[PDB]
Amino acid sequence: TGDERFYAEHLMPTLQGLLDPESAHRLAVRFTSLGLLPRARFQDSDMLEVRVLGHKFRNPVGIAAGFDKHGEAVDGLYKMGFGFVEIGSVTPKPQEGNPRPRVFRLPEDQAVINRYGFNSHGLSVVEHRLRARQQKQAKLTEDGLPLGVNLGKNKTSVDAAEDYAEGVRVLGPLADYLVVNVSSPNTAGLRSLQGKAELRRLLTKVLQERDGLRRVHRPAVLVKIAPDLTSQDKEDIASVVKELGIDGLIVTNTTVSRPAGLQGALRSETGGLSGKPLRDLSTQTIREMYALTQGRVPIIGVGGVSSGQDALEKIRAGASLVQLYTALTFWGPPVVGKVKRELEALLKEQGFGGVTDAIGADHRR
Ligand SMILES: Cc1cc2nc3c(=O)[nH]c(=O)nc-3n(C[C@H](O)[C@H](O)[C@H](O)COP(=O)(O)O)c2cc1C
Ligand SMILES: COC(=O)/C(C#N)=C1\SCC(=O)N1c1ccc(OC)cc1F
Ligand SMILES: O=C(O)c1cc(=O)[nH]c(=O)[nH]1
């Protein structure tokens, strides 16, 4: 489309020329919340519908955690054409996150590095924000547009599992699915929660708390994992997810690695790397986790999706749904419809009747 080119060649590089990335993101959140967005001409076809996690999803393309950290732009994001929205990470208490600058663009790599450190309005603020549109969300959910809430831990917390449990109690009842984010690279010690013994203790507490919620307010619980795990760590996570009946996995968070070949001047900034250089590392992690869980555990695939091909590769590797963030940063809102249009085209070319038929297809080759 004309919009796709104008955004990608004029609008977004102009905004990028004028504003540091944190400013630009704040402005984007504001515009989205106000619905100041291009017409999302693409109409979701039936071949894009997916049923998973106890819900219908109109299309399989979601906004990944971190874009709407505090639940300010949910309805704007649906307007953009996302099949599902994930907010967060939310921490129990408000906290500022790290000092600025803390986000960096690598335009020559189609990548970003961030070290926000869980800047969060906190659970209470977010709770009230979601409660203000709770029945609007219930109607959206019923219409195939579910809401996920991603939970974090405060920096100075003395009991990580208690932070997650507090999140489950507070925001669980307002979410279709919850995400235990134990893979930020920007909170000290957090990724050690992916270890077998820590994860089993943590997840048992999280699941107990979730199962204590009233039926109609009981969300699915997913775990979001890093792209930098060892084979032992992957194995362990798969074992615990089966042992406990975790509902799904989000694969992956940003990478602490710096793949050879990065060109951006800012490549050696501390933080998590997202975008194109993370793409195949995340696809491979999806593939491994789908096989370790025997294809029985839904996966939301994320990292470096910017086209229909990128989405289909993750679907074929084992994702039931995909998310993106960094593509939006570079191409703007039209990227969403682009991905969907291209995905539908490729599904037809590859002889799939819909998305559902393509889930895990590479493992049946
Ligand atoms: C600026 C920024 C903030 C993010 N914040 C969060 C967060 O709060 N919680 C989380 O689980 N993931 C967060 N992520 C990771 C994304 O959700 C996603 O997993 C990652 O960016 C890979 O997707 P992408 O390559 O499409 O951006 C963040 C990523 C970026 C770039
Ligand atoms: C001065 O800033 C604008 O004009 C923006 C912005 N930001 C506009 S104009 C129409 C539009 O869609 N956006 C926008 C909204 C969300 C974004 O997510 C990255 C990016 C955008 F460019
Ligand atoms: O807040 C952040 O720094 C953040 C959290 C997270 O989970 N992933 C990420 O890349 N950044």
Image: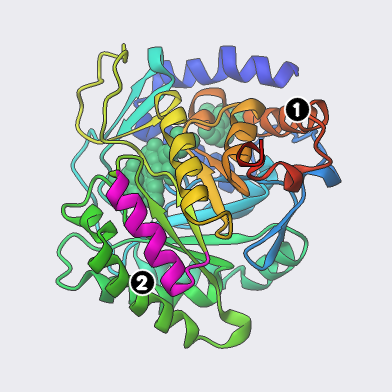
Quarter assignment of residue 6? top right
User: Which span of residues is magenta-colored?
Assistant: 231-247
Q: How is the image coloured?
A: rainbow
Residue tagged by mark 2? 203
User: Is residue 351 depicted above or below 11 in this figure?
Assistant: below
User: How far apart are labels 2 and 1 at the CA level?
Assistant: 38 Å
Q: Amino acid at mark 1?
A: Leu
313 and 190: which one is in front?
Answer: 313
- Residue drawn at x 52%, y 20% as measured from the top left: 12
Quarter of the image with the C terminus in it: top right
- Residue drawn at x 18%, y 59% as measured from the top left: 155
User: Is residue 18 depicted above or below 132 in this figure?
Assistant: above
Magenta includes 234?
A: yes
From where the camera sits, is residue 27 visible?
no
Residue 8 in the figure: left or right of residue 94: right
- Return the x and y of residue 359 as percentages of the image width and height: 66, 45
Residue 187 in the figure: left or right of residue 322: left
Q: Which SS type dominates the magenta stretch?
A: helix
Q: Amino acid at mark 2?
A: Leu
Quarter assignment of residue 209? bottom left
Residue tagged by mark 1? 346
Name the quadrant where ligand 2 sits. top right
